[PDB]
Length: 372
Length: 18
Image (cartoon, rainbow over all chains, first blue to last red):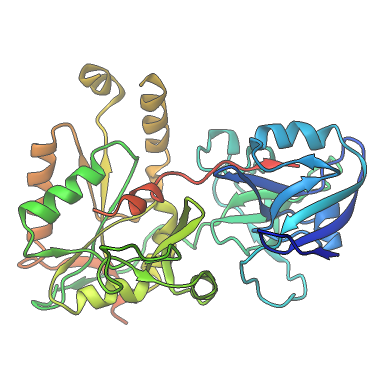
Protein backbone atom coordinates (compact mmCIF):
# COMPACT_ATOMS: atom_id res chain seq x y z
CA UNK A 1 0.00 0.00 0.00
CA UNK A 2 1.23 3.48 -0.93
CA UNK A 3 0.17 6.97 0.18
CA UNK A 4 1.15 10.24 -1.47
CA UNK A 5 2.24 13.10 0.78
CA UNK A 6 1.47 16.82 0.41
CA UNK A 7 5.03 18.11 0.72
CA UNK A 8 7.25 15.06 0.96
CA UNK A 9 7.49 11.98 -1.24
CA UNK A 10 5.26 8.94 -1.63
CA UNK A 11 5.32 6.64 1.39
CA UNK A 12 5.09 2.84 1.47
CA UNK A 13 2.89 0.92 3.92
CA UNK A 14 3.80 -2.69 4.70
CA UNK A 15 2.50 -5.14 7.30
CA UNK A 16 4.74 -7.71 8.97
CA UNK A 17 3.81 -10.09 11.79
CA UNK A 18 5.96 -9.87 14.92
CA UNK A 19 6.23 -12.51 17.64
CA UNK A 20 6.62 -11.59 21.30
CA UNK A 21 10.32 -11.45 22.23
CA UNK A 22 11.27 -12.63 18.73
CA UNK A 23 13.16 -10.07 16.56
CA UNK A 24 12.02 -9.49 12.97
CA UNK A 25 15.54 -10.00 11.66
CA UNK A 26 16.23 -6.49 10.40
CA UNK A 27 18.75 -3.94 11.63
CA UNK A 28 18.44 -0.16 11.72
CA UNK A 29 21.04 2.58 11.71
CA UNK A 30 20.70 6.31 12.28
CA UNK A 31 21.48 8.59 9.38
CA UNK A 32 20.98 12.04 10.89
CA UNK A 33 17.50 12.16 12.44
CA UNK A 34 16.35 9.29 10.24
CA UNK A 35 15.93 5.61 11.03
CA UNK A 36 17.13 3.49 8.12
CA UNK A 37 16.69 -0.23 7.53
CA UNK A 38 20.36 -1.06 7.01
CA UNK A 39 20.36 -4.87 6.79
CA UNK A 40 17.97 -7.79 6.29
CA UNK A 41 18.95 -10.90 8.27
CA UNK A 42 18.17 -14.33 6.80
CA UNK A 43 15.80 -16.53 8.79
CA UNK A 44 13.61 -13.82 10.27
CA UNK A 45 10.07 -12.70 9.50
CA UNK A 46 11.41 -9.50 7.92
CA UNK A 47 13.33 -11.49 5.32
CA UNK A 48 10.60 -14.04 4.57
CA UNK A 49 8.01 -11.35 3.87
CA UNK A 50 10.33 -9.49 1.51
CA UNK A 51 8.57 -6.28 2.51
CA UNK A 52 11.57 -4.56 4.06
CA UNK A 53 14.57 -3.49 1.99
CA UNK A 54 17.99 -2.11 2.86
CA UNK A 55 17.77 1.67 2.66
CA UNK A 56 14.08 1.90 3.56
CA UNK A 57 13.50 4.82 5.91
CA UNK A 58 11.14 4.07 8.79
CA UNK A 59 8.79 6.99 9.37
CA UNK A 60 6.19 5.28 11.54
CA UNK A 61 5.41 1.91 13.10
CA UNK A 62 1.88 1.35 14.43
CA UNK A 63 1.16 5.06 14.81
CA UNK A 64 4.46 5.78 16.55
CA UNK A 65 6.75 8.52 15.29
CA UNK A 66 9.98 6.65 14.52
CA UNK A 67 11.78 9.48 12.71
CA UNK A 68 13.93 11.39 15.18
CA UNK A 69 14.53 8.40 17.43
CA UNK A 70 17.94 7.03 18.34
CA UNK A 71 18.25 3.43 17.15
CA UNK A 72 18.73 2.45 20.79
CA UNK A 73 15.19 3.70 21.40
CA UNK A 74 13.90 1.89 18.31
CA UNK A 75 15.62 -1.23 19.62
CA UNK A 76 13.96 -1.02 23.04
CA UNK A 77 10.61 -0.21 21.45
CA UNK A 78 10.28 -3.12 19.02
CA UNK A 79 11.56 -5.50 21.69
CA UNK A 80 8.37 -4.65 23.58
CA UNK A 81 6.13 -4.98 20.52
CA UNK A 82 4.26 -7.90 18.98
CA UNK A 83 1.42 -8.75 16.62
CA UNK A 84 0.84 -7.05 13.28
CA UNK A 85 3.32 -4.24 12.72
CA UNK A 86 2.31 -1.59 10.20
CA UNK A 87 5.35 0.19 8.76
CA UNK A 88 5.26 3.58 7.07
CA UNK A 89 8.37 3.81 4.91
CA UNK A 90 10.15 6.04 2.47
CA UNK A 91 11.11 3.20 0.10
CA UNK A 92 14.83 2.61 -0.48
CA UNK A 93 16.50 4.33 -3.41
CA UNK A 94 19.18 1.64 -3.50
CA UNK A 95 19.43 -0.80 -6.39
CA UNK A 96 19.57 -4.48 -5.46
CA UNK A 97 19.70 -7.12 -8.23
CA UNK A 98 16.65 -9.28 -9.13
CA UNK A 99 16.14 -12.05 -6.52
CA UNK A 100 18.66 -14.86 -7.04
CA UNK A 101 18.08 -18.38 -5.71
CA UNK A 102 19.56 -18.68 -2.23
CA UNK A 103 23.08 -19.97 -2.87
CA UNK A 104 24.83 -21.43 0.18
CA UNK A 105 28.62 -21.64 0.33
CA UNK A 106 30.24 -24.00 2.83
CA UNK A 107 33.62 -22.97 4.18
CA UNK A 108 36.09 -24.11 6.82
CA UNK A 109 37.58 -21.45 9.08
CA UNK A 110 41.35 -21.40 9.51
CA UNK A 111 41.30 -18.62 12.09
CA UNK A 112 39.62 -17.79 15.40
CA UNK A 113 37.01 -15.04 15.57
CA UNK A 114 35.38 -13.48 18.62
CA UNK A 115 32.99 -10.65 17.61
CA UNK A 116 33.25 -9.13 21.10
CA UNK A 117 36.90 -8.39 20.31
CA UNK A 118 35.83 -6.78 17.04
CA UNK A 119 35.37 -2.99 16.99
CA UNK A 120 34.18 -3.04 13.38
CA UNK A 121 31.20 -5.40 13.81
CA UNK A 122 28.16 -3.45 12.50
CA UNK A 123 25.63 -5.13 14.78
CA UNK A 124 27.23 -6.72 17.85
CA UNK A 125 24.10 -8.72 18.69
CA UNK A 126 24.53 -10.52 15.37
CA UNK A 127 28.20 -11.34 15.84
CA UNK A 128 28.92 -15.02 15.21
CA UNK A 129 31.92 -16.58 16.95
CA UNK A 130 33.92 -19.49 15.52
CA UNK A 131 37.20 -21.37 15.94
CA UNK A 132 39.79 -22.97 13.64
CA UNK A 133 38.19 -25.98 11.99
CA UNK A 134 34.59 -24.87 12.40
CA UNK A 135 32.42 -25.25 9.31
CA UNK A 136 30.42 -22.17 8.32
CA UNK A 137 27.34 -22.15 6.10
CA UNK A 138 27.59 -18.78 4.37
CA UNK A 139 24.01 -17.91 3.38
CA UNK A 140 24.67 -14.36 2.18
CA UNK A 141 27.67 -12.49 0.81
CA UNK A 142 25.68 -9.47 -0.38
CA UNK A 143 27.86 -7.43 1.98
CA UNK A 144 31.45 -8.38 1.00
CA UNK A 145 32.79 -7.29 4.40
CA UNK A 146 30.10 -9.01 6.46
CA UNK A 147 28.77 -12.43 5.49
CA UNK A 148 25.62 -13.89 6.98
CA UNK A 149 26.25 -17.42 8.17
CA UNK A 150 25.26 -20.25 10.47
CA UNK A 151 27.89 -22.23 12.36
CA UNK A 152 27.52 -26.01 12.13
CA UNK A 153 27.14 -27.44 15.62
CA UNK A 154 25.35 -24.36 16.91
CA UNK A 155 23.17 -26.18 19.43
CA UNK A 156 20.62 -23.41 20.02
CA UNK A 157 17.74 -22.86 17.61
CA UNK A 158 19.38 -19.92 15.86
CA UNK A 159 16.99 -18.90 14.06
CA UNK A 160 18.74 -15.83 12.65
CA UNK A 161 22.00 -15.94 10.74
CA UNK A 162 25.12 -14.37 12.21
CA UNK A 163 27.70 -11.93 10.91
CA UNK A 164 31.22 -13.07 10.05
CA UNK A 165 34.22 -11.20 8.55
CA UNK A 166 34.31 -11.33 4.76
CA UNK A 167 38.00 -12.01 4.33
CA UNK A 168 39.46 -12.89 0.94
CA UNK A 169 41.66 -15.95 0.58
CA UNK A 170 44.82 -15.00 2.44
CA UNK A 171 47.51 -17.63 1.95
CA UNK A 172 50.49 -18.29 4.22
CA UNK A 173 52.86 -17.27 1.44
CA UNK A 174 51.65 -14.92 -1.29
CA UNK A 175 53.69 -14.88 -4.49
CA UNK A 176 55.21 -11.47 -5.22
CA UNK A 177 56.79 -9.76 -8.22
CA UNK A 178 58.83 -6.58 -8.62
CA UNK A 179 57.05 -3.58 -10.13
CA UNK A 180 58.90 -0.46 -11.23
CA UNK A 181 56.85 2.73 -10.98
CA UNK A 182 56.74 4.26 -14.48
CA UNK A 183 57.93 7.86 -14.76
CA UNK A 184 54.59 9.23 -15.97
CA UNK A 185 52.29 6.78 -14.15
CA UNK A 186 52.63 7.28 -10.40
CA UNK A 187 51.11 4.75 -8.01
CA UNK A 188 48.22 6.17 -5.94
CA UNK A 189 49.47 6.74 -2.41
CA UNK A 190 46.77 5.47 -0.08
CA UNK A 191 46.61 6.10 3.66
CA UNK A 192 44.82 3.88 6.18
CA UNK A 193 44.58 3.49 9.95
CA UNK A 194 42.77 4.95 13.00
CA UNK A 195 41.04 8.33 12.76
CA UNK A 196 42.86 10.91 14.90
CA UNK A 197 46.41 9.73 14.19
CA UNK A 198 47.17 12.76 12.04
CA UNK A 199 46.28 10.98 8.81
CA UNK A 200 44.13 13.81 7.44
CA UNK A 201 46.79 16.27 8.60
CA UNK A 202 49.65 14.51 6.80
CA UNK A 203 47.60 14.51 3.58
CA UNK A 204 46.98 18.26 3.54
CA UNK A 205 50.60 18.86 4.51
CA UNK A 206 51.56 16.90 1.38
CA UNK A 207 48.92 18.48 -0.86
CA UNK A 208 50.10 21.98 0.12
CA UNK A 209 53.84 21.80 0.87
CA UNK A 210 54.32 19.97 -2.44
CA UNK A 211 51.31 21.11 -4.47
CA UNK A 212 52.83 20.41 -7.89
CA UNK A 213 53.25 16.65 -7.44
CA UNK A 214 50.12 15.53 -5.62
CA UNK A 215 46.46 15.54 -6.65
CA UNK A 216 43.14 14.24 -5.38
CA UNK A 217 40.64 12.05 -7.20
CA UNK A 218 37.46 14.01 -7.92
CA UNK A 219 34.77 12.28 -5.85
CA UNK A 220 31.10 11.94 -6.71
CA UNK A 221 28.20 13.42 -4.80
CA UNK A 222 24.41 13.53 -4.92
CA UNK A 223 24.49 16.95 -3.27
CA UNK A 224 23.27 19.70 -5.59
CA UNK A 225 26.26 21.80 -6.74
CA UNK A 226 26.77 25.12 -4.93
CA UNK A 227 27.49 28.61 -6.28
CA UNK A 228 31.30 28.73 -6.22
CA UNK A 229 31.67 25.06 -7.14
CA UNK A 230 32.67 23.62 -10.51
CA UNK A 231 31.07 20.46 -11.91
CA UNK A 232 34.47 19.19 -13.02
CA UNK A 233 37.01 19.60 -10.23
CA UNK A 234 35.11 19.97 -6.95
CA UNK A 235 32.79 17.00 -7.39
CA UNK A 236 31.15 14.99 -10.11
CA UNK A 237 27.65 16.21 -9.25
CA UNK A 238 25.19 13.44 -10.11
CA UNK A 239 21.62 12.39 -9.30
CA UNK A 240 21.02 9.83 -6.56
CA UNK A 241 19.93 7.21 -9.10
CA UNK A 242 23.17 7.62 -11.04
CA UNK A 243 25.16 7.27 -7.82
CA UNK A 244 23.14 4.24 -6.73
CA UNK A 245 23.61 2.72 -10.18
CA UNK A 246 27.37 3.26 -10.05
CA UNK A 247 27.47 1.63 -6.60
CA UNK A 248 25.75 -1.48 -7.93
CA UNK A 249 27.99 -1.46 -11.01
CA UNK A 250 31.03 -1.71 -8.73
CA UNK A 251 32.23 1.68 -9.95
CA UNK A 252 33.11 2.98 -6.46
CA UNK A 253 36.23 2.33 -4.41
CA UNK A 254 34.51 3.67 -1.32
CA UNK A 255 31.26 5.53 -0.72
CA UNK A 256 29.48 6.90 2.34
CA UNK A 257 26.59 9.12 3.39
CA UNK A 258 26.87 12.64 4.84
CA UNK A 259 23.90 14.85 5.68
CA UNK A 260 21.35 12.97 3.55
CA UNK A 261 23.67 12.95 0.53
CA UNK A 262 26.04 10.31 -0.84
CA UNK A 263 29.75 10.85 -1.37
CA UNK A 264 32.28 8.48 -2.89
CA UNK A 265 35.54 8.08 -4.79
CA UNK A 266 35.11 6.25 -8.09
CA UNK A 267 37.74 3.93 -9.58
CA UNK A 268 37.84 6.05 -12.75
CA UNK A 269 38.48 9.15 -10.63
CA UNK A 270 41.78 7.65 -9.49
CA UNK A 271 42.68 6.16 -12.87
CA UNK A 272 42.31 9.63 -14.38
CA UNK A 273 44.69 11.12 -11.81
CA UNK A 274 47.23 8.36 -12.43
CA UNK A 275 47.13 9.14 -16.16
CA UNK A 276 48.00 12.79 -15.47
CA UNK A 277 51.48 12.02 -14.16
CA UNK A 278 50.51 13.22 -10.69
CA UNK A 279 50.48 11.26 -7.43
CA UNK A 280 46.94 10.45 -6.34
CA UNK A 281 46.52 10.97 -2.60
CA UNK A 282 43.64 9.13 -0.98
CA UNK A 283 42.49 8.21 2.52
CA UNK A 284 40.35 5.08 2.78
CA UNK A 285 38.74 3.02 5.51
CA UNK A 286 40.48 -0.36 5.92
CA UNK A 287 37.19 -1.94 4.85
CA UNK A 288 37.46 -0.46 1.35
CA UNK A 289 40.87 -1.99 0.63
CA UNK A 290 39.14 -5.03 -0.88
CA UNK A 291 37.61 -3.11 -3.78
CA UNK A 292 40.81 -1.11 -4.20
CA UNK A 293 43.24 -4.01 -4.62
CA UNK A 294 40.91 -5.83 -7.02
CA UNK A 295 41.34 -3.05 -9.56
CA UNK A 296 44.43 -2.40 -11.68
CA UNK A 297 45.28 0.81 -9.81
CA UNK A 298 48.51 -0.67 -8.38
CA UNK A 299 48.13 1.25 -5.10
CA UNK A 300 50.82 1.80 -2.46
CA UNK A 301 49.11 1.49 0.91
CA UNK A 302 50.73 3.14 3.92
CA UNK A 303 49.46 2.34 7.41
CA UNK A 304 49.39 5.35 9.73
CA UNK A 305 49.57 4.32 13.39
CA UNK A 306 49.75 5.93 16.85
CA UNK A 307 52.57 5.01 19.27
CA UNK A 308 52.33 2.57 22.19
CA UNK A 309 49.67 2.90 24.90
CA UNK A 310 52.22 4.32 27.35
CA UNK A 311 53.67 6.74 24.79
CA UNK A 312 50.13 7.84 23.91
CA UNK A 313 49.59 8.68 27.58
CA UNK A 314 52.73 10.82 27.58
CA UNK A 315 51.51 12.92 24.66
CA UNK A 316 48.11 13.17 26.36
CA UNK A 317 39.81 12.08 25.38
CA UNK A 318 40.16 8.87 27.40
CA UNK A 319 37.61 7.16 25.17
CA UNK A 320 39.85 7.99 22.21
CA UNK A 321 42.98 6.13 23.34
CA UNK A 322 40.85 3.05 24.01
CA UNK A 323 39.49 3.21 20.45
CA UNK A 324 42.86 3.64 18.68
CA UNK A 325 44.73 0.87 20.45
CA UNK A 326 41.74 -1.43 19.97
CA UNK A 327 41.93 -0.85 16.21
CA UNK A 328 45.65 -1.56 16.38
CA UNK A 329 45.14 -5.13 17.58
CA UNK A 330 43.17 -5.69 14.36
CA UNK A 331 45.94 -4.57 11.99
CA UNK A 332 46.99 -8.20 11.43
CA UNK A 333 45.63 -8.37 7.87
CA UNK A 334 48.76 -6.58 6.64
CA UNK A 335 47.60 -5.56 3.16
CA UNK A 336 49.64 -2.37 3.51
CA UNK A 337 53.20 -1.91 2.25
CA UNK A 338 54.67 0.03 5.18
CA UNK A 339 53.55 1.38 8.56
CA UNK A 340 54.35 4.82 9.95
CA UNK A 341 54.25 5.36 13.70
CA UNK A 342 53.15 8.99 14.00
CA UNK A 343 54.50 10.55 17.17
CA UNK A 344 55.59 13.86 15.69
CA UNK A 345 53.90 15.13 12.51
CA UNK A 346 57.18 16.56 11.22
CA UNK A 347 58.95 13.26 11.88
CA UNK A 348 56.07 11.31 10.35
CA UNK A 349 55.80 13.63 7.34
CA UNK A 350 59.47 13.36 6.38
CA UNK A 351 59.31 9.57 6.66
CA UNK A 352 56.08 9.62 4.63
CA UNK A 353 57.64 11.80 1.93
CA UNK A 354 60.78 9.66 1.87
CA UNK A 355 58.63 6.58 1.28
CA UNK A 356 56.63 8.24 -1.49
CA UNK A 357 59.74 9.64 -3.18
CA UNK A 358 61.53 6.28 -3.08
CA UNK A 359 58.95 4.86 -5.50
CA UNK A 360 60.62 6.80 -8.33
CA UNK A 361 64.03 5.13 -8.08
CA UNK A 362 63.37 1.86 -6.24
CA UNK A 363 61.04 -0.94 -7.49
CA UNK A 364 58.53 -2.56 -5.12
CA UNK A 365 57.00 -5.95 -4.36
CA UNK A 366 53.38 -6.36 -5.44
CA UNK A 367 51.19 -9.46 -5.63
CA UNK A 368 52.19 -11.34 -8.79
CA UNK A 369 48.54 -11.23 -9.88
CA UNK A 370 48.84 -7.47 -10.41
CA UNK A 371 51.38 -7.96 -13.21
CA UNK A 372 49.95 -11.12 -14.75
CA UNK B 1 40.01 20.35 1.36
CA UNK B 2 36.58 18.73 0.99
CA UNK B 3 34.82 18.79 4.35
CA UNK B 4 32.33 16.09 3.36
CA UNK B 5 34.99 13.55 2.31
CA UNK B 6 36.66 13.74 5.72
CA UNK B 7 33.34 12.89 7.36
CA UNK B 8 32.64 9.73 5.37
CA UNK B 9 36.03 8.45 6.57
CA UNK B 10 34.61 8.19 10.08
CA UNK B 11 33.19 4.77 11.09
CA UNK B 12 29.63 4.06 9.85
CA UNK B 13 26.66 4.35 12.27
CA UNK B 14 26.22 1.33 14.54
CA UNK B 15 23.33 -0.97 13.69
CA UNK B 16 20.79 -2.40 16.10
CA UNK B 17 18.52 -5.43 15.79
CA UNK B 18 14.74 -4.97 15.73
